Image (cartoon, rainbow over the protein chains, first blue to last red):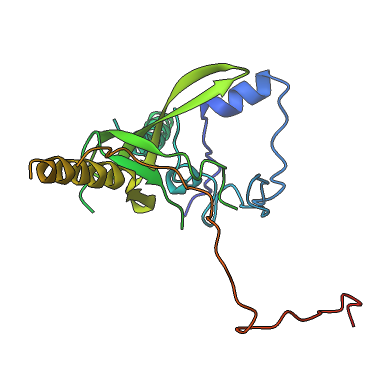
Length: 88
Length: 116
């Protein structure tokens, strides 16, 4: 088989090369939160992403479903970006 | 349980993530799996209105209105009886009246606050 030297030319790499933004160091999943006395990692197990839905007070039409819809729309936008970059 | 707009309910809870417990209100909006209760807040001395949304799992009906209906029914019954009394207004707790107590029941004793 040939050598898969080809890589992803996604716009992010070009922007990072142009900008001075150094790549993230991937410190860890353990983010910190308040009012719980626990780390509650960002993503990986019962993270803060679902905390807004789990919490029983949304003081501000159902707003709980709107956050999930927004997250799904962001995921769809990421998928669209992946599809666009796949043509590179 | 079944809930409808305008029903008076209390914010039940089963660390709490906030201190909104005990803020009674009236449900102004209902949906598939959520309800909306109106609550009042204030800054300084100026009262303000606040819209509040809660999960139905931690809401219970308010029993405050039951006393009013019971009093209305009692007043109606008193009025009906009057046709065959007066002064049907509620009376406050009156002070205790004089009474005689015999020492035979229990002779006074000394409890010696030494204590011991």
